[PDB]
Length: 129
Image (tube, rainbow, N blue to C red; front, side, top):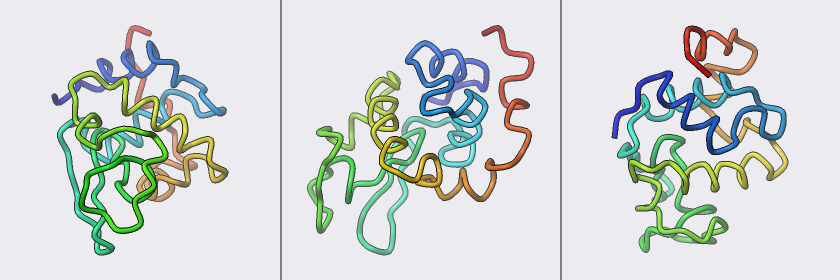
């Protein structure tokens, strides 16, 4: 599924991401924009042989199991395919563990490079939340 901007904001808010670990909803919408362009089915292979999955491009080495990744830990205890669902619940649950891991949203390199420090509130501007 390809979410609309305000549609994704509302879904992320309903699943308790607004201000989770102190990150406003615009931070999460901005991260999803640059990780996946709001497409739940986005996948990207990394040079280390891992793959990133879903709206927040969660990786198969630490977080989800895809059956083909060396050094796999599956810390979210989920098949990576669950992160491609139209239902963002698995992505949100796994993102909450990632952002709790010590480095906050710096875990998402696109968030650090394209969202951090910017006027992230613009990503929820106009939305009925």
